[PDB]
Amino acid sequence: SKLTDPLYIKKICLEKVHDWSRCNEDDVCVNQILSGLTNQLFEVSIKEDTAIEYRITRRHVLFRIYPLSEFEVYKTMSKYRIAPLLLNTFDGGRIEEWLYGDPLSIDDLKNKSILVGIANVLGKFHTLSRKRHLPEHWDKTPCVFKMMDRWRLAVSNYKNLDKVTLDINKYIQESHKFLKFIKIYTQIENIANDIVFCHNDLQENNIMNTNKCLRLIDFEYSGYNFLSADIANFFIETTIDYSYNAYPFFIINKKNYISYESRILFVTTYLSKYLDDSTAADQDIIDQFLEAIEVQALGLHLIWAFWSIIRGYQTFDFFLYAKERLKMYDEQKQYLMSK
Ligand SMILES: Nc1ncnc2c1ncn2[C@@H]1O[C@H](COP(=O)(O)OP(=O)(O)O)[C@@H](O)[C@H]1O
Ligand SMILES: [Mg+2]
Image (cartoon, rainbow, N blue to C red; front, side, top):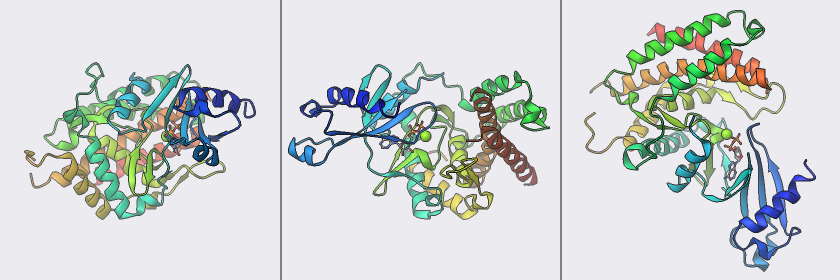
């Protein structure tokens, strides 16, 4: 695999990237980068002296080897320059614009100026639905209903769930109680309940930063959802570090949950890009908005716990991670019911 993959990759890029066929396999550099289990990813480049030699302008590409089709969404996202530009396709993968920065770190999410930048970008991203014409066949049923329903059904079919938690049926029961609550709750006249085209996996590793220019990647879970669910996911992710490089390959720091003041600064910045100048906007917009986010956070914990259980059964400690997201459900629920 590791020794044989590069040669395959080199041949395709030579013929699928403009001007690269001027080179040979010896001028091209393949480097596998870290990814999820759903794809293999490689930084492919040309040797820099050879790029200057052969006057090659595009020095790097991303080589990607493989409800809503991820691909269909990705190509719409690329069209509007939200995602890295699609360069080309081959059977089994795609070649994308290479982004020069780095994913945001978990500690970046503490920086207020970065939070502001994320809120600006997310505020704009969320207007796409009303400002462009998205493919109309896309299901507009909020992904919270779909993900919760689909993934809970699948977890109910498993044997040995007590090997995840003694109290698993409590959370299977919690889920449809949440869906019924969320059916009523999101009918409140508040923009947090707007249904827009959502990323659905908003987190530091999906936000590329090039010299203070923030880009979004990874549209695998993308679809229409309550706008506050995209934001709740981001807020949650301030307490989860996936960079940790030994078992269980994630670290939870709940003390790091984005502070109240940072949350108001994020929501305010967000609304300054999401809302039109002429928006019909009440006094408690921020209060209700911050409340809807915490409400959605509750469901996300279930959604991602069930997701992680399915991955555990079909394959990072997925089960410990589910367990942790369930403890978060419990904690979040106490919090909500408090106020
Ligand atoms: N177009 C790109 N340019 C440079 N780096 C990328 C690009 N796309 C992804 N990466 C890197 O690979 C990682 C995973 O990419 P992504 O597709 O979002 O995740 P996954 O492969 O887990 O679905 C990112 O954190 C980023 O560092
Ligand atoms: Mg990702």
